[PDB]
Image (cartoon, rainbow, N blue to C red):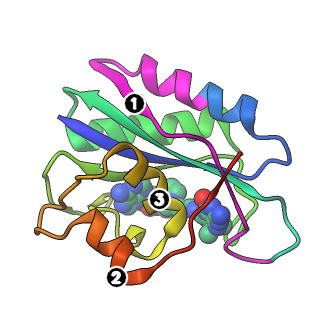
Amino acid sequence: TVAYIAIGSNLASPLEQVNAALKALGDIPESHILTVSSFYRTPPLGPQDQPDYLNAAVALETSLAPEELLNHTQRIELQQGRERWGPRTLDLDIMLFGNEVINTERLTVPHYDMKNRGFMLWPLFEIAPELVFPDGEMLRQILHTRAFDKLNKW
Ligand SMILES: CC1(C)Nc2nc(N)[nH]c(=O)c2N=C1C(=O)NCCN1CCC(SC[C@H]2O[C@@H](n3cnc4c(N)ncnc43)[C@H](O)[C@@H]2O)CC1
């Protein structure tokens, strides 16, 4: 199954942190990275004084069950990270999990708010321009409809 994961960090210098998380995702059991988006520099969603964020998307091939993958992402955030409107040492959000629709106490997929977040959508559109959501919405359509500003690379 292909899962798409969003990564964000707003350490003043987040590259080492993001590469650590990326290595950790690749080391997840029964899983491997297919593709990584470019690294993007985004203005803080939240108070405007804190450091710019680095966002990216990852396509992860996995044989894990959805809640198992989440167990790993929470673990990586704990091991590599350390709140509300930022700063964020390290977030890993499961955006999509194959074509699965999940609505449980722990996990909502597609991610509940990505349709509103250009820092999530644009990196994803870089690696999966043809992506169709489980309900038939098109990633391309969402970006066309909303006209989110394009992002500068890191
Ligand atoms: C400060 C803020 C708003 N501003 C930003 N500005 C820019 N420019 N860029 C950013 O990047 C950026 N980020 C920001 C941010 O603050 N993101 C956290 C989102 N994010 C929520 C889920 C969990 S943190 C809460 C809870 O959500 C649960 N969850 C439910 N569904 C899911 C799911 N699909 N994927 C993952 N977690 C799930 C999870 O169990 C956890 O307990 C992990 C992280």
User: Is residue 86 or residue 61 the one in the foreground?
Assistant: 61
User: Is residue 68 or residue 91 the one in the foreground?
Assistant: 91
In front: label 1 or label 2: 2
Residue 85 spot, x, y in % from top left = 69, 72
Label 1 crowd (10 A; few <14 / some 14-19 / many >=20)? some
- The amino acid pointed to by label 3 is Trp
Residue that appears at 54% across and 34% down? 76
Residue 106 spot, x, y in % from top left = 33, 58
Q: Quadrant where the C terminus lies? A: top right
Which disc is residue 145 wearing? 2
Q: Which residue bears the numbered disc 1? A: 35
Q: Quadrant where the N terminus lies? A: top left
Residue 54 spot, x, y in % from top left = 67, 49
SS of the residue under disc 2: helix
SS of the residue under disc 1: strand
- The amino acid pointed to by label 1 is Thr
* Residue 151, placed above or below residue 6: below
User: Is residue 87 or residue 123 the one in the foreground?
Assistant: 123
SS of the residue under disc 3: helix
- The boundaries of the magenta stretch are 21-47
In the picture, residue 51 is in which quadrant?
Answer: bottom right
**Disc 2 beta carbon < 8 A from ligand 1?**
no
Q: Which residue bears the numbered disc 3? A: 122
User: Which of marks 2 and 3 precedes in the sequence?
Assistant: 3
